[PDB]
Length: 51
Length: 50
Length: 49
Image (cartoon, rainbow over all chains, first blue to last red; front, side, top):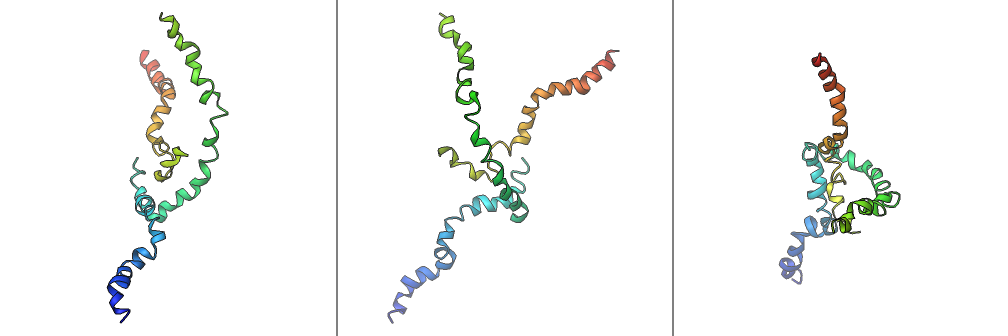
């Protein structure tokens, strides 16, 4: 009972986004080096290469 | 696709920060002489124009 | 170190070394005349006759 009432506010507010975001939240703040830098390395095979 | 491009920047570390960052003091041009190479002569217009 | 606010985000850190292939023509501008002395002068002398 003390748990089921808190599913929508303490569990779902986290279990929805903990493991994708909040669990790697310290790793989330270095995804800006993924989408912009190291995933751009996968695109650096062409984008800087053609230049 | 990252891996074929992940093999450049790893060794690019030991290529840049040891050499370029030094060359401001050895070159007298950097801030000592080129700041007035022209200004020894080419700014004669400060008095040759008058 | 204000000048470092952009260096890392170039992937290849230098802004113009990735451009060096395009900038290479400007560096060879001194040696462009050597190309004129290499084959074009050799071409010129032959056709001068």
